Image (cartoon, rainbow, N blue to C red):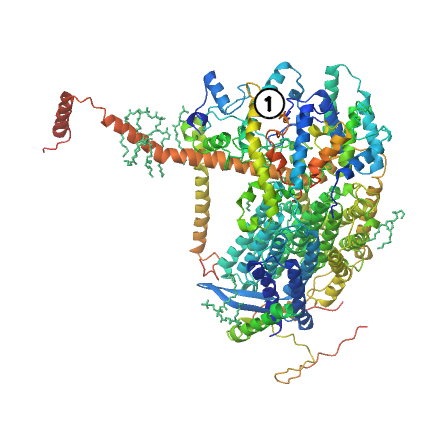
Amino acid sequence: SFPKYEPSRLASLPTTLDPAEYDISSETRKAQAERLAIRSRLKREYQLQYNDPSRRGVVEDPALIRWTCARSANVYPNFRPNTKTSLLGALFGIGPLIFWYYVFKTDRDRKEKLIQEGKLDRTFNISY
Amino acid sequence: MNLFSSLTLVTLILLTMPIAAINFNTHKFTNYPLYVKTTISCAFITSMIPTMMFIHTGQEMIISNWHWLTIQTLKLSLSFKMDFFSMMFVPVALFVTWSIMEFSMWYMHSDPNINQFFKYLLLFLITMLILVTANNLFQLFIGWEGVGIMSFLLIGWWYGRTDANTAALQAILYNRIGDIGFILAMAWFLINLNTWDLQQIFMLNPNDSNLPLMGLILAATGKSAQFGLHPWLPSAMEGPTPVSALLHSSTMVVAGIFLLIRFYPLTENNKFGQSIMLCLGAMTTLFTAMCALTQNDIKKIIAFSTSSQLGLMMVTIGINQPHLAFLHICTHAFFKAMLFMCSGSIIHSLNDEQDIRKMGGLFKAMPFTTTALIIGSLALTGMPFLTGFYSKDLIIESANTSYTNAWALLMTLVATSFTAIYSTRIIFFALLGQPRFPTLININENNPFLINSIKRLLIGSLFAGFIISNNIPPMTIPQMTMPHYLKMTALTVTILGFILALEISNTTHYLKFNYPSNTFKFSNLLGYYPTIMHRLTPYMNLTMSQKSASSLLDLIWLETILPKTISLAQMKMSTTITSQKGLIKLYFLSFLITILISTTLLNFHE
Amino acid sequence: DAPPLTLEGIKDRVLYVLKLYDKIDPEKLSVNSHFMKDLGLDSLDQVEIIMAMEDEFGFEIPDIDAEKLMCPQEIVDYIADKKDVYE
Amino acid sequence: ITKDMLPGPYPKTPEERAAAAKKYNMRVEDYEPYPDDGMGYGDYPKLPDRSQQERDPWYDWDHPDLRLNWGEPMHWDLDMYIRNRVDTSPTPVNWNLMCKHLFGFVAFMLFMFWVGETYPTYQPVGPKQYPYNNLYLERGGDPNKEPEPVVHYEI
Amino acid sequence: AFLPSAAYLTHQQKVLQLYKRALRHLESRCVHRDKYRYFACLLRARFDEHKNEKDMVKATQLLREAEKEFWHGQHPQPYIFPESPGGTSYERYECYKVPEWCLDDWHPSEKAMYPDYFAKREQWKKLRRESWEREVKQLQEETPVGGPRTEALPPARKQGDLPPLWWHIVTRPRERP
Amino acid sequence: SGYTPDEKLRLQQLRELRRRWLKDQELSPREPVLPPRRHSIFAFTHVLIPVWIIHYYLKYHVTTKPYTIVEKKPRIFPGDTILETGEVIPPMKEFPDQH
Ligand SMILES: CCCCCCCCCCCCCCCCCC(=O)OC[C@H](COP(=O)([O-])OCC[N+](C)(C)C)OC(=O)CCCCCCCCCCCCCCCCC
Ligand SMILES: CCCCCCCCCCCCCCCCCC(=O)OC[C@H](COP(=O)(O)OCCN)OC(=O)CCCCCCCCCCCCCCCCC
């Protein structure tokens, strides 16, 4: 009848087609009301400072500061060298270095061997 | 000589004078747009004199007036090439820009930053005439990057809108991908020919011109939005309608086509480059015209129209007809700027409504816009002896009668039928039928700015192909002998496109509901190409820009190997040295072991 | 261009659309005529009325705001709030 | 900002997981960190990897262009899922079907351009005939040499 | 799903939102007004056929396959209003929506160009800064323990008092500055 | 159903304050209180003086230097007369007339 929509990484499943949206249980109402309570407490704590006439400046968000501290400063203190990190750091670290080394060395050996035999047309080449 | 070069440079300096006027301001201007429009009117009038005295004799010259920079054997001078290409494209661009700015004095009238808008639009015009009057690759690169940056600043005009910033950065991205090939071309010409000047490039005339012409084709694919580097030109409809009308119809988007036309002595001796240009132009003019058939935003339809016509220009370059391609540039400018201006008149009259499914009944309510839109569509499809007849039909007469990639020819003719299909789609859903826009009618087009600005491009779209194509000198030999099914190819295929799309239009009034097919969803979702590539290619970059490059390498591993392991080594050796228990017995026992290793193990007494 | 909206004009246009709707008689109708309690209209009819408001004034009302417009005066006041009338 | 509101190490004990969930202002049932393979995340939550375009555009957001509230834990790639960038919104056609259609169309067109290059069209004519030894001097041929005579005849 | 005051979507809300989305995508499919009007009545009949379903599991299942019907039969480029998200004029004027606090940063020689406006502005500023502590003590005497459950704000429960957290709703910029 | 009376009262009060704000955005007729502040001049200042300047620059600083302005030599036809010399270009051969 109908083709089932297959969600991918760059195209997620719609809310209208997800089965877990149609849960009418009590515990999902618990989780949704608790998320509403946490979000309402965050909203209230925001706009009690946002609407303040005495405040003049930047409402500091601990979520944003926490995000930047995770993206920059917490990376090395929670690094553990193991199999996956060693293979990915040697695969994406020195793999391209080896690759471009052999490509550029091969191209320049071919070019120098053509030049010292008089084969490469270097006729009007006086800028280098 | 003294008149030609004088008015040549007076045109350009006259364009640069209102930039000094807007940069040296203190007051609120008494209608700076009227000042810039008068300036461009006078620049058009000034540029018509060297054009007339090029029609008279064929007078070409070079003004290498200012010695700028000598890199040991490369003398870069400020050099202006006044040939056929400059002499025709400069007055057409000035005339079109004059109409676009008299349109802009009305369309952008409520904008509080209208003086910045006319400043940016004049800076675009200055950089484009730097591009087309350039004589070396460096000054052409100046004009090239200049029209790219003014494209950025004019797409992202409403910069608070996220999608305008996104489309502007998209257009910059695709143009820099083309600039890779342009700088490849400049690199090849400097290393192999010791020049960026066009004269030494053309006089040395290399036969190993595969690599620089591939670079120039990549540059034109970036700039003219050919296939692979196409979607930014539909994305570039996010800017205002004069931006989509001047830059993205007629003037900037032909700069890649103009770049390949400028290097016609190199493409005329490279059959492989001609084959690549023919295949790429036919692919582009098929794909964009096919995507145009199912769109509903009117500016997107006209953007796929102008990218299809740029693909047709790349086709007629690829069949070794560069002067017909440049004639099609100068032809296409008039009616495509006019089609964008008529669509913008409809958009402004319907309270910023751009979707054609909220239009209709505009045949009589907007009579002048309807008249000029129908004249523009007939010039686009190639009604006989309108302006689009005097190049495009001849293009088909040279596309059939040449040693041609036959699949490229057949897709060019299918695209020619598709042009008629989307033209009558515009006329049907916009002008015909009954209204679909809301109930508070504020339809009005009684501004003399709007009327005169569409009127001059209307006179252009009626007469300019005839005037130009009878004023140009013959630069090739026109094929005028062909069989009667072949002479009647373009006209019959265009009429069949009209008839098939009349069937398509009349099947929309039927009281039947159909499910969308895969051809329809393939055309409506832009060949799936901005959906996949604008989700996939950022993803595999940006994760790699963070997880691989930022986090793993330059926050962890390159941080691990040199400083952290050495620091931990010094910490551990420091703790091994200084963990002594303060016991004199153990220190003298160490001294004993020192003396024994000194005598028996190292022989420091022998 | 773009003539300004007034509460009298928005009221006249909203009641003009509701008078062109066959499930509402024009003499019972007022600005306080509740759709479910006075006019006896379905919730589907209320959704169609809000869609007619969208097609009339040319902008989209979100559904979380659409499902609370249960009289013409609240519709007129929402269009007043989203078009900023009586400046 | 203080230290125990900053991100820390990977939580293992359930009170540490609940303290992390309280720190990032989310439920313990919804707090899932990145799995401790040693990639440098720590206690940072693995938010569900959706774009910001997918959010409710009519909701009263604290940051309207970001579509993001105050104190809500940001995604690790929040600068990547901004609306200027990667969108993971659902598409009407399936992703794999889109990739197959685009790949098949491009491959078929390039195949048929190669076919037409193998079998080109032409006109039933002879070669274009040029005088003066196929224009020997005009094509830069040197006059101190003498080419072969190219002779054309009437027909 | 995601709502400011409601914690979920009822079955009735899901049905009405599906009904509106189906009519909008149908109007995108069925461009002409008489033809859409015909098929809109047919779709209204399809929605009215299962309106009296007291079995909630059967009704939720019918809602689910109706969503599948919708996801199959949607237009790839549906119509979007211009100032609606995804529209061609959406968030266009946000670059012109300069906030009001920047008027505090003006030079006095350009504040003296509009003396009535800033003299009329200072009483708004005074009104807000006297209303602030009253609406803070109104919020803390009405919010339950554990914080507010919903994002719904109360009105002013006295006379003369302003509603709590009112300044950025009232002094928001116009849509067309 | 629709609103609750709490939401009705709040949105009514916010609507009243919003309309008062939008009213107080208006302009007094004395405002803006400003501080106290040749027919073809465009063809003279933007055209004729630039033609003067650019012709002076091209005539006495550009063409005084070699190869700065290099013009293509004029196209010569059979039957022409050279202005510098007076040499008449001889005409072509008589045509083998075709029609
Ligand atoms: C309103 C102001 C205008 C002037 C008002 C007052 C004067 C009135 C009118 C008289 C004209 C002025 C007197 C004559 C002018 C000077 C004549 C002269 O010999 O000048 C010496 C020279 C002429 O060139 P030159 O070759 O003699 O000297 C160059 C110097 N060497 C040789 C050492 C390298 O300089 C100029 O004239 C400078 C004018 C520059 C104008 C264009 C600027 C373009 C800026 C772009 C920068 C980047 C370019 C990069 C790309 C370049 C190409 C690849
Ligand atoms: C004659 C030969 C012809 C050959 C033709 C084909 C050659 C090129 C092949 C394909 C490469 C280019 C296309 C892929 C990248 C496109 C990126 C782009 O434009 O992304 C746009 C995207 C937003 O797009 P969209 O979703 O439509 O926006 C409207 C609603 N938001 O915006 C974003 O998501 C923001 C992204 C920002 C970061 C960009 C990361 C990707 C960078 C890619 C670099 C590619 C370098 C190529 C080098 C080629 C060298 C020869």
Q: Quadrant of the N terminus of chain D?
A: top left
In this view of the protein, which residue sits in the foreground, B232 or B269? B232
Which corner quadrant of the image does residue B324 belong to?
bottom right
Residue drawn at the location 43% of the way across and 43% of the way down: A101
Residue C60 at least partly seen: no
Indicate left or right for A42 with B576 as reference. right
Q: Position of residue B416 (x, y in %)?
A: 75, 50
Can you tell me whether the CB of the residue at mark 1 lies under 8 Å from the nearest atom of ligand 2?
Answer: no
Residue situated furthest front in the rendering: E160
Q: Quadrant of the C terminus of chain D?
A: bottom right
Q: Position of residue D153 (x, y in %)?
A: 72, 69
Residue D2 at least partly seen: yes
Circle 1 residues within 10 Å: few <14, some 14–19, many ≥20: many
Indicate left or right for F16 with F70 as reference. right
Q: Position of residue C1 (x, y in %)?
A: 74, 48
Residue for badge 1? A36
Q: Chain of mark 1?
A: A
Depicted F41 relative to depicted B305: above or below: below
Q: Position of residue D99 (x, y in %)?
A: 64, 35
Indicate left or right for E47 with B547 as reference. right
What amino acid is found at the position of numbered circle 1 in the picture? Leu
Which corner quadrant of the image does residue F75 belong to?
bottom right
Q: How many marks?
A: 1
Secondary structure under the numbered disc 1 in the rendered image: helix
Depicted B445 relative to depicted B435: above or below: below
Residue situated furthest bottom in the rendering: F86
Residue situated furthest left in the rendering: B606
